[PDB]
Amino acid sequence: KIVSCRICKGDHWTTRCPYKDTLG
Ligand SMILES: [Zn+2]
């Protein structure tokens, strides 16, 4: 449908986000 990140809301899911440092 529509791809939207959950960390920066760019152009890529939350998995392929260039800032998935939210792993901890
Ligand atoms: Zn992102």
Image (spheres, grey):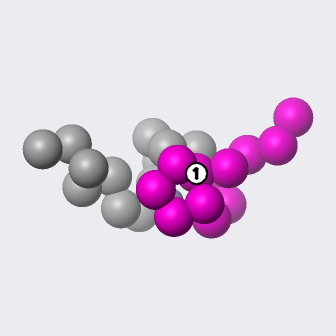
Tell me the kind of residue under disc 1.
Cys
Residue 11, percent across and down?
A: 67, 60
Q: Quadrant of the C terminus?
A: top left
Q: Residue drawn 82% across and 43% down?
A: 2
Q: Quadrant of the N terminus?
A: top right
Q: Is residue 6 magenta?
A: yes
Q: Residue furthest top?
A: 1
Which stretch is magenta?
1-12
Secondary structure under tag 1 reads loop
Q: Residue furthest left?
A: 24
Q: Residue drawn 36% across and 62% down?
A: 19
- Is 4 left or right of 14, judged from the image as shown? right
Given residues 6 and 13, the one toward you in this image is 6
Q: Residue drawn 33% across and 52% down?
A: 20
In this view, 8 is above or below 12: below
| Mark 1 residue crowding within 10 angstroms, few (<14) / some (14–19) / many (20+) | some
Q: Main secondary structure of the magenta part?
A: loop
In this view, 15 is above or below 18: above
Residue 6, percent across and down?
A: 52, 49
Q: Residue drawn 46% across and 56% down?
A: 7
Give the quadrant of residue 21.
bottom left
Q: Is residue 8 magenta?
A: yes
Q: Is mark 1 within 8 Å of ligand 1?
A: yes
- Is 12 left or right of 3, judged from the image as shown? left
In this rendering, the count of numbered labels is 1
Residue 3, percent across and down?
A: 73, 46
Q: Residue furthest right?
A: 1
The residue identified by callout 1 is 5
Residue 10, percent across and down?
A: 62, 65
